[PDB]
Length: 35
Image (tube, rainbow, N blue to C red; front, side, top):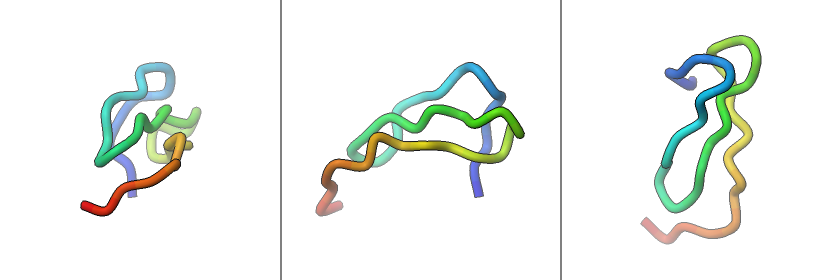
């Protein structure tokens, strides 16, 4: 459940989520995040 355009990414929880190409998906570096 992402909310962004493809080619913009942004800051999420404890990592950055690169908006996929469908405008509704994200990669998110995903390294760690206790809260």
